[PDB]
Length: 97
Image (cartoon, rainbow, N blue to C red):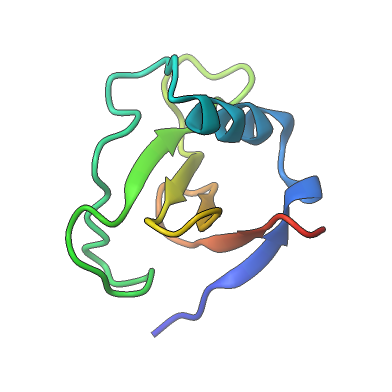
């Protein structure tokens, strides 16, 4: 009961580009929670079995904490979602734009 919009890769902040690069490489990640399973408890992303989704920090420039920006990856190649509000809303990353 909220759809998922789309955001163009080109329109993401440079730190999100950094995160995506790190996920492609397998690390290194700055925070201990980077790579843990995202449970999708609120049902905002499509329902899958547990383990389908993993979460990664997107650094917020000038923040002393992990902040609220994240990439969630799904099991399918290039299936990535960006949130800037600690999972209150998501947009699917569109690599073709």
